[PDB]
Image 1 (cartoon, rainbow, N blue to C red):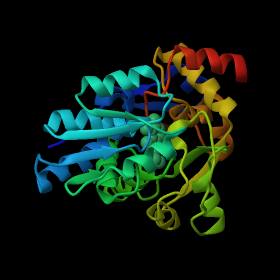
Image 2 (image 1 turned 135 degrees about the horizontal axis):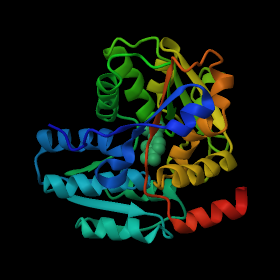
Image 3 (image 1 turned 180 degrees about the horizontal axis):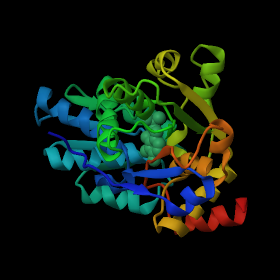
Image 4 (image 1 turned 180 degrees about the vertical axis):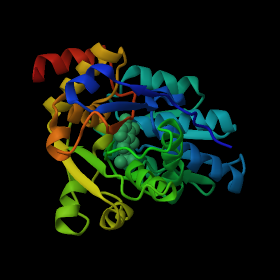
Length: 315
Ligand SMILES: *Cc1c(COP(=O)(O)O)cnc(C)c1O
């Protein structure tokens, strides 16, 4: 069936009180490998093996949580994995990949360069695993909504807050909502100002290309958003919103204090709409009779030293 697991939907009572609205947190940090990537990437990897067999090699350099998901899936599926990460990568990320039995290569100043290098390593029976832009990834991610429907007792929420990098998760959410007949549920698509290709693309009505962007929200860096994201944004209620690195960092700190979990600034971006109350400015109708769902995407590009740095720099 699938490599991902059903995850908890936690009530956030201090937030619910503060916001005068029910806040639920969808906990993707519980997935094998530590992030929501397990859904999308799990689906891609599973299908690749069903079609191509177990003599393939998975190849990936497309971001920290993608490579972790690929490493995990390759071990579960009994397949070779070739993984590239930037020269200065978090050591536990490296150890996890080695422990899985993947072949780890250290290369590049950032994840874009790791990806560029990884792409050149794909041989005749190798398959490159993208982070976001593939139909299988969207299908995999869409499983989150089927779960949400059950967990919320078929009551459509007032909004779903969804971090956006390349738009894979976004696409699965919107597609899941259409399949669930929740076509009217707004998705708040959150990015940081440092890399806002989705938001910029919606303004332009075409795919904006960005180079050299950086942000603490590593998994949200993308040169462009998927063409599918822009297409779906025309036919479903989507609100693009951007927050600062300082807001995302503060949310990571607050979530660690409140829920005792360390999540990436990527997930912190979505949580920041609640912690800052900006959600109320976006949806002025919110009331204690209404529900908001935050997709807490998890991620492994976070550590105690990140939290030291965030506190010093942004607070
Ligand atoms: C992949 C990911 C996202 C959203 O990514 P897309 O590229 O838009 O699919 C958000 N948070 C984390 C931690 C991720 O790994």
